[PDB]
Structures are given as structure tokens and as C-alpha cells.
Image (cartoon, coloured by chain):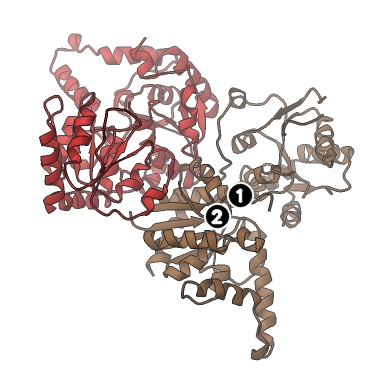
Chain colours: A brown, B red
Amino acid sequence: SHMRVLFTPLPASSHFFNLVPLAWALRAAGHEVRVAICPNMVSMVTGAGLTAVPVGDELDLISLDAVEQLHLVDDRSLDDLMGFAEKWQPDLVVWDAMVCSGPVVARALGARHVRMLVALDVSGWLRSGFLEYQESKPPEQRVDPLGTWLGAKLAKFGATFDEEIVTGQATIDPIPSWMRLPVDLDYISMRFVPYNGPAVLPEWLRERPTKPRVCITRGLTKRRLSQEQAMVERLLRGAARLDVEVIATLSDDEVELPSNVRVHEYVPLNELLESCSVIIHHGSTTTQETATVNGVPQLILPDESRRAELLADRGAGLVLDPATFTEDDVRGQLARLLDEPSFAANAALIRREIEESPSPHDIVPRLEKLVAE
Amino acid sequence: SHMRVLFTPLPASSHFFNLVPLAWALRAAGHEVRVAICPNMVSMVTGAGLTAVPVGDELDLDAVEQLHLVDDRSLDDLMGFAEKWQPDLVVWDAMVCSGPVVARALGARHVRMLVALDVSGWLRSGFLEYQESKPPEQRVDPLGTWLGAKLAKFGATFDEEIVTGQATIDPIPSWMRLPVDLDYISMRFVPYNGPAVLPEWLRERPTKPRVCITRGLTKRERLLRGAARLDVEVIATLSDDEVREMGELPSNVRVHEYVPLNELLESCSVIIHHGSTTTQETATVNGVPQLILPGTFWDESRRAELLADRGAGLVLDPATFTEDDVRGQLARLLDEPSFAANAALIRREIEESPSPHDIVPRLEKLVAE
């Protein structure tokens, strides 16, 4: 190997999946890559071909000082992580923007660390306001609740607070440039490469569809909880009203369905989207990014609002209000998305833009440079 | 450059695991990657984070047609998927003929991948030279005829490249390579050994040399006991692989059903195994001296023998091996700084070979040619 690399994701499909191609990029380059995950998510990490380091107590993040657990910075988990990081001595920590696990350990060890976004850098942008506010107050007044909080976690291991602990020494950004919230940081642009969990191509997904194909879905994390409810029934019936094949992802639950609807518990999303003409979703980053990367016009029922808006602004999608929309709304917008050639044309442009930003493969030498400096 | 790439592995964990890092390298570079596999093994593919394409009938290892995925069932299935998907590139495990036949029929580029020493290619060049030296009416090609027939069903003709690829990716260290004249692409072996979870026992630093003993790889007689009992004669901790009753294991043998091999090997002083590629390579890149009881069913002895020639391992002839042999040879691997020093040199040479990441533009260019 050359580097030892430790990822600290948030234990949630959507977050984890977003890091997988970068982690495989590093591994493909001969780096050793390990993923720290709570012990009950281990088989999600292992299901992506990555090596898991179980750390801390079981954590059902979906059901959830409880603030500490969600940021992975509770004694049990942090001490456990740090026990492993001390023996393994990684050179680089790539940490998911919503945990403080990774940067705390990194700074404690003197490792380099990089933040990865899954969504718009809301954190970064809030923190930007805060620092701007702070700068103009008198020195004696420059309080920093986050700073001093992280300072205490850091002291437990004999290290000090730094701004980097909040926003990383760099931030890898998989959302397209032109959506980026305006904040002054070292962003590394990275092409989104879809990973959606275990993917088997069933025979039927081998053929060109014979009728326009519409995918209706919501992010894997968003589906685990998850009256009322009737919104999906409305989307489904709304979309059925056109001469299209409708593929929908649902739990065991219902219902009697239009003859042109097909319901599955799971599909391989990226591979389905290659054959779809429209996707309808609730604005999870990964379903959105997977559609965008396949250049597939979107109907979004909402940072999801903002990402949905931004995408409509470039005419690649349309939005509907999750709390006021009617079957007929669904019908009409779907029709626009299918009939007006511009929508697909714009989506094709955004796709080409993305296809031209550096891949995970191209980010590896930048990370290597960062560790070697 | 945005390619569609199809992998067609032999459906066996040794062979497939050998392709995983290159497959991910391609996907990490933004290419679309799919792996055709027989239905009973889609799980091994998806468990490596890769997209599986179930093709053909259940297979468990015509007869030779099945072994090489070139029975109608497989071929037809693959071909019907490939016809529609139109891959730009097919990477194929050296023991299979599905990938190249299919690539040739669609006009896709294709590249063959070794998992062992290129015995096929060595044989084939022998055959081509003996053929070249015969008068023309005598230059018969059983293998060529037999493939030519399979290409026929799809309207394509035979080429030598159906036998040895347009290029061959070689992950075995190149100093071991059989002398044969082909366009080999050297590639750094990057270990993948199935689902890997760091267990608590691996958290503790070793208190004396760890010696790992694994049934040469997932493949899968009580010569295994000859092996365990004899390494216990040294002050070493064995980590050995299985559940099984054969009596009293000495106290220093620690039994574990599952180990994560790569991670295990980072704290081992010695590994004892049956010579399989995945195991020998994973140890080689971790720089662990090796004691090998090769069989068997291919190039294990030549590989084992080549490690021993560079002084990075010792071999034992099974059938005739004794418990005193194992203790003597093992004691040699632990006491002579030689073996670790040579294992370190060979490891460090492997680290200068282009990684799967480095090979990507090389394949992108091949497709673009």
C-alpha cells in the first residue's frame, strides 16, 4: 500500500453509498481503506466490498446527549474509534459532513482529514454566517458554542480545536458545482458515481421498453420510517393516467392498481434509470443524483426543496407541493416532462457537465498530494 | 471516455475475487461495469459491491462446454444480454470462452485476465509453432475448429485472439511469467477476499509470531492435522481455519471459522497454505514468508517453487511430508531473517507495478484505438 485511509460515515445507506466509489477508487489505487461503522451496519459496508471496522454500540439512527450519538462523538463510540485509530495510524480520514467522529480522531492523531458532503453544505454556510458575525463583535464577545464543545471532546485526547474540525482541511463535493451554496472553502469537485446497494439485473430490465417508462421511488434511508401516505397512492394513480409503464417501489402495503403499474420492493435503481424517460421522487440526494447522472427528467415532491428548485431552474425537472398536489397535477407535469423535448435536452446538458468533472479515480492523486504535503 | 464494460469470470470465488479491484477501478473512473455470472452466484458479485447479470443455468464445480461457459444455455443468454447492452469492452477470465466469443460477435474490444501462470498461452504457442512447422494441409486446429463453430452460430469467424485476448492483464509478479510472446499488461495484485470485518481478536497486537494456516482458499486430507500439530511445536500462535473434530488441538492453536485474510496477514510472520493464487498473492503483497504444500490441480507447484527460488518461502511435498518437516521449515521461516527480507523485496517490487487504477487509461485507450 501507500496510504492508510479511514472513512467515518454516518450509519445511513444514503450517506454510506455516497462514499463507496471514492473508497473503491482509493483501494484500486493500492491504498488500504477501512470503514468505521456501528456494529449493526457492518454488513452494509461489507455488502459494498469494503472492509468494516465495528465501532461503538449498536445504533438505530433511523429511530433517533442524543446529539452526541448522532454525530458519533459519544464516549463509547469515539473512545472505541480512537482505540483503533491509534493502532492503525491512518494517514487520511475521509468523514461524512454530519459526524465529528472523524475529524476529532484525525486531529488527535495528526492525520490529514477531508470532509465529504452528501447534500448542499448547509453546515458550512451556517458556520460561514457565524464566523462573519463573530469577526465584527468585540474579542471578549466572540463566543463559539460549537468551538468550545468540540474543544472539550478534543481535550479528552490532548488536542486543540481548529476551524478545520468543523469544515475539514478540504471538502469533497459530489453535488454539481453550479448548485454549490456560496461559501469560502477548499472544495474538491467530484462526479457523482451511483452506488445503490446490491444490484441484480433481472431479465426484464435487459430489453428496451416498448412504452415510455416512468420510475417512481424514494431513497432507501427515506423509506425506513416512513396515514399519510395517500400521497404515494396519488402519485401512482396520477402517473398511471398516461400511456406509460410505471415502475414503483413500495413496501408490502397498498392499494388495486392500474394495469400499467408495476410494483417491486427493490430495484437496481441506476440500471433501471438507464431505461426510464422520467423519474418521480421525494428529493433524496442519491435518487436525485442517480437520475441526474443518467440525464433523466425529474418530478420532485420535496435541502431537498432547494436542490429540486435548482434543478427546475435549469429546466430538467419540475416540482410539486407534497402537501397540496392532486392526481391531475401529477398527470400534467408528467406529460410536460415526457412531451416537451427541452426537459430531456437540459437534463442531457447537466449530464454532460457532470461527465466532465473529475471522477473519484481523478480525485485520488489530489488526496495523495494532500497527504504528502 | 465513458465505456460500458462487461466482465465474464469463471464462477468461482478465487477467480472472481481476482477481478474485483479492476472492476471497481473502472467504475471509480466513471465507467459502467457489469459482471455476468451464473444464477447461483449473483451473491458473490453483489457482495463485492458490483452489478450482477445472471446468465445461464446453475453451475457447480457438454462438460467441458459448461466449464468454459460455452454451452448453449450460457452463450445464448450472455449473447442476448450483450447484443442489447453493447459493451465497448469485455474483460474475461482466462479459462472461459464466453466473453471473447461474445466480444468477437459484437465487435467489442476484449482483454483476457490471468488468475494463474499463463499455462494456456504457453501451450498454445507451443502448439502454434509445431503447427507452423507442418505442411499447410496438415495444420489442424482442434481448438480453433471448435471455437470457429461457436462463432459460426453468431456470424463471426475465429481469430487467434479468441484464445489469448487482444491483450492479457497479468496480476502475477512478472518475474514468474511463463516465456510467451503476447501483449501482457502487468498489474499490481490488490487483495480482495470476500466480506471482511475486523474481529475483536484482531484488535490485539500479537504476543508471539502469528502463523496463519488456511485451507489454500475457499476450495473446499487430514494432512491438515499434520500441518496444525507441527506448527504448534514452535512458540507461535496459529490461527487456523475451520470447524472440525480431529481430537485435541494444542493450546496455541486458535481456531476461527472466518478470518478476514488480508487483514489477518498484516500481523502474521508466516502463512501455510495449499498454493492457490488468491492466497499466495495476498501473502506476497503483505510480504509474509510462505510455507506451501501445493497440490494439485494446476500451477501451484511452479508458483510455490518460484517463491522458494527467490527465497521468500519453502515448499513441502505433501503425501511424503512429516510433522518434523513442518516444524523444521517453519522454524526456518521464523529464524532466518532471509525469508522476511526476500518477501519484503518481492512485495516492494509488486508495489511499483501499475495499480488497477493505473491500468484504467490503458484500457480506455485500447477501446478508443
Q: Is residue B317 visible?
A: yes
**Against B78, is A139 above or below?**
below
Residue drawn at point x = 77 percent, y = 31 percent: A253
**Quadrant the C terminus of chain B occupies:** top left
- Asked whether A22 or A198 is in front, the reply is A198
Q: Is residue A205 left or right of residue B226?
A: right
- Asked whether B190 or B119 is in front, the reply is B190
Q: Is residue A98 visible?
A: no
Q: Is residue A250 left or right of residue B197?
A: right
Q: Is residue A301 left or right of residue B123?
A: right
Query: Circle 2 is placed at which residue position?
Result: A9
Query: Circle 1 is placed at which residue position?
Result: A12
Residue A116 quadrant: bottom right
Q: Categorize mark 1 by other alpha carbons within 10 Å: few (<14), some (14-19), many (20+).
A: some
Residue B324 quadrant: top left
> Residue A341: where, in percent of width, then height?
74, 41
Kind of residue at disc 1: Ala
Chain name for mark 1? A
Kind of residue at disc 2: Pro
Residue drawn at point x = 76 percent, y = 51 percent: A312
Q: Helix, strand or loop at disc 1?
A: loop
> Residue A239: where, in percent of width, then height?
81, 34
Q: Are marks 1 and 2 in contact (CB under 8 Å)?
A: yes
Residue A173 quadrant: bottom right
**Against A158, is A252 above or below?**
above
Q: Categorize mark 2 by other alpha carbons within 10 Å: few (<14), some (14-19), many (20+).
A: many
- Asked whether B284 or B67 is in front, the reply is B284
